[PDB]
Length: 268
Image (cartoon, rainbow, N blue to C red; front, side, top):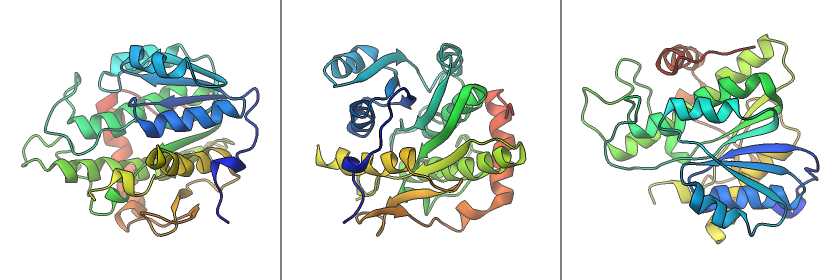
C-alpha cells in the first residue's frame, strides 16, 4: 500500500521551520512532525490564531510571527532562527483579487514565491538538511512574465496569477538545487504538492500534508517533486512537471529577477 504519515521516521532532536497560512495543510504537517519528536517553529501572520491551535498539539509546536507580504518581517523572523534542519515553504494564498504587498509585489507572487525566496536565502547558512517548497497542479498553465512579474501593465487573472506563483515555486527549487550542487553543499531542495485541494476544481488536509511529509522525510534526489500519482489523487511518489518548469534558462533568469526584487542573494 502507499506511503502515509503513519510511516514517518523519527524527527527527535530535529528542528523544522514551517510557514503557515493558519490553514489545515500547514497545521497537519506541523502536527505529524511534532508527534514524531520534531521541534516545530510555525511562522504565521496571525500568531493569536496560531498559538490557540499549537498549544493543544502533541509534541513541540512553537508559534512565531512572520508576514511573507513584508520583507522587513521576513528578515526579522529569519534573524531569530539560530538554526534549523528542514525548512518547509508551505504558506500560500490562492486565486485572490488583485492586491499589492508592502513591497509593491502582486500578492500571490509576492507571498507564495518572493517572500519564500527571501526567507530561504536568509536561512540557508544555518540549515542542515533540506528545503521543501509546496507547489500545485496549477503550475501547469502558468508562465513566468519577466518583464511584468507583478501584473502592473497587464489585465489580472486570479488563477493565472496563482499559476505563475506555483510555477515559480518549481523553478525556484530547480535553480536552488543547481546552486547547492555547484557550491558543494549537502543540502537538498525538493518540492511537493497536495493534489486536488489547491486546484481550480480534516481529510483534505491529511491528504495534502502527506505529500509534503514524504518530501520532508524520505531519501530523495535533489530537485525531486513529490505528489499523488494521478495528480489530483493517487499514491505518494515522485511525479512529473510541466515543460516550462523544466526550462533551466528561465529558472536562472527568474532567480536573478527575484534577487533584485527582494534584495537577497544566494549566500553559499
